[PDB]
Image 1 (cartoon, rainbow, N blue to C red):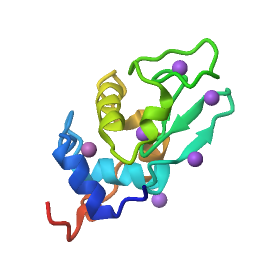
Image 2: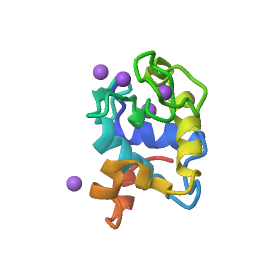
Image 3: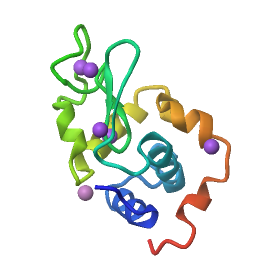
Image 4: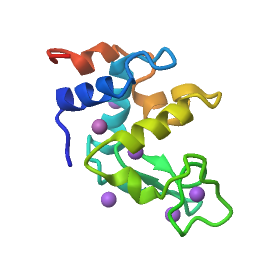
Amino acid sequence: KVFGRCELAAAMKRHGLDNYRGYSLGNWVCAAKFESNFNTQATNRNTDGSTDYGILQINSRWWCNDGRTPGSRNLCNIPCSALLSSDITASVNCAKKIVSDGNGMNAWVAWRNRCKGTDVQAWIRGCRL
Ligand SMILES: [Ag+]
Ligand code: NA
Ligand code: NA
Ligand code: NA
Ligand code: NA
Ligand code: NA
């Protein structure tokens, strides 16, 4: 599923991401935009052989099992394919664990390079929320 901007903002809000560990909703929408272009089906291979999955590009190196990332962890206790559903529940719940692990949203490369320190409120402009 490719979400609209305000559609994703609403889904993220209902799932408890607005101000989760102090990160406003706009941060999460911005991160999803630049990680997956709002596409739940997005997958991308990393140089180490792990893969990033879904709307928030969650990586198999630490967070999920994709059956092809040897010597990795599965800290969200999920198959990576779960992160590809049209419904974002699994991605959100796993993201909450990631953002809580010590590094905050810096875990998301796209967030650190494209959202951090910008006017992220713009990402929810005009959205009925
Ligand atoms: Ag949902
Ligand atoms: Na893909
Ligand atoms: Na992989
Ligand atoms: Na994801
Ligand atoms: Na893994
Ligand atoms: Na940018």
